[PDB]
Image (cartoon, grey):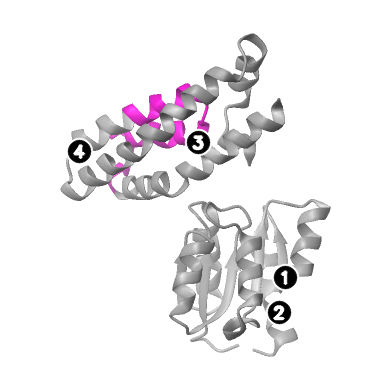
Amino acid sequence: ADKELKFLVVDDFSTMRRIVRNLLKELGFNNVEEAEDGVDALNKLQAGGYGFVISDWNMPNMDGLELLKTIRADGAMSALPVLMVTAEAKKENIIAAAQAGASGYVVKPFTAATLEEKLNKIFEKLGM
Amino acid sequence: KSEALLDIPMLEQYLELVGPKLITDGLAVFEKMMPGYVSVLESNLTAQDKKGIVEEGHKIKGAAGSVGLRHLQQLGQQIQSPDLPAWEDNVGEWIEEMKEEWRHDVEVLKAWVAKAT
């Protein structure tokens, strides 16, 4: 897609950010800002300009599922692509995400190969 | 993730012998003292008082440990250990992380205690 596309990596403080930020730099994307949780994220998102969200599921103040929900509700950014990247592989977690309108799901641990395919899949489907 | 946050082996023992009262009572004290602690931490960081940071870390590590909040205890373990390689570069993030999740951790603990009993 476009190289100037703005991403927001929502992850408290684990290895997810260093991994994802790096894999994104490799695919060509350099415009990447990070957040610690749903709250911080929503604030940063109000500034506008963002075109893609990548987030964990378990974070304090607001988990990934609530953030997902909050994003879909808000009309100004109801279509913003959101990709969940979490350890949670149960039946409840995946269905919740599908119902809420997740763009995609990636289970941890994952490999660079997968994350790149999950991104490139969503890029086609949406036409970025 | 509830296992990476709590010291389950310790808590299950507490429940068997004594009961939940001591944990909740102790957690009650922690919830009151904690806000003060992080504030003092934050201060010493900007002021760059090395001994300050280390000392307060030792206090939170103990405070958290006694009530079974494993990740906090661990996060305090690192802050009070300035001999660790690249302590200076990574210490600030461990503090911002302490400030970010302490309340959530407390919540996950109360929750587990209820369900447990």
Residue at 49 percent of width and 25 percent of height: B67
Q: Nearer the viewer, mark 2 or mark 3?
A: 3
CB of mark 1 within 8 Å of CB of mark 2? yes
- x then y, percent, for residue A91: 83, 54
Instruction: Specify whether B31 is left or right of A104.
Output: left
User: In the rendered view, does A63 fall on the left or right side of B53?
Assistant: right
* Numbered disc 3: secondary structure: helix
What separation in Å lies between label 4 and label 2 (alpha carbons)? 47 Å
Indicate the position of residue B55 as horizontal and vertical percent values.
25, 30
Above or below, comparing residue A23 to residue A61 in the picture: below
Residue A50 vertical placement versus A60 (above, below): below
Q: Could you say where residue A30 lies in the image, as x and y percent from the top left?
A: 46, 78
Give amino acid for label 2: Ile
In this rendering, position of residue A25 left or right of residue B81:
right
Q: Which residue is labeled 1 in the image?
A: A104
- The amino acid at mark 4 is Lys
Q: CA distance from mark 1 to mark 4?
A: 45 Å
Q: What is the distance, in whole Å, between disc 3 and disc 1 at their CAs? A: 30 Å
User: Are the residues flagged by discs 3 and 1 in contact, CB closer than 8 Å?
Assistant: no
Disc 4 target residue = B50
Q: Residue at x 48, y 85 (%)?
A: A49
What is the magenta range? B59-88
In the picture of the structure, the residue carrying the numbered disc 3 is B71
Callouts 4 and 2 close, C-beta under 8 Å: no
